[PDB]
Image 1 (cartoon, helix red, strand yellow):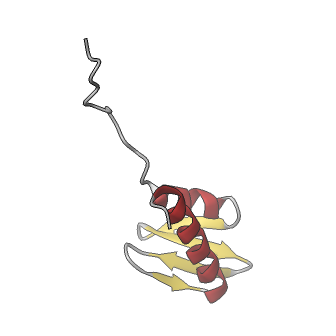
Image 2 (tube, rainbow, N blue to C red):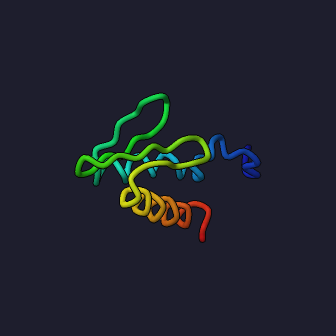
Length: 77
């Protein structure tokens, strides 16, 4: 029998980037362009790249808040 359970099969509990997309999309209109994530709200726009964000400061501050809270959820902060 497999009573030991040395295998978990799959482990997807670090997908913070996925939740960023979902949460931002639930509050703002989000567009995917140049394989980046664009957050748009009130004609303001922001671009999230692999390791940097450039965009409207209001959106950026919100993005950062969302990222950090979500980071706290999976990685703990």
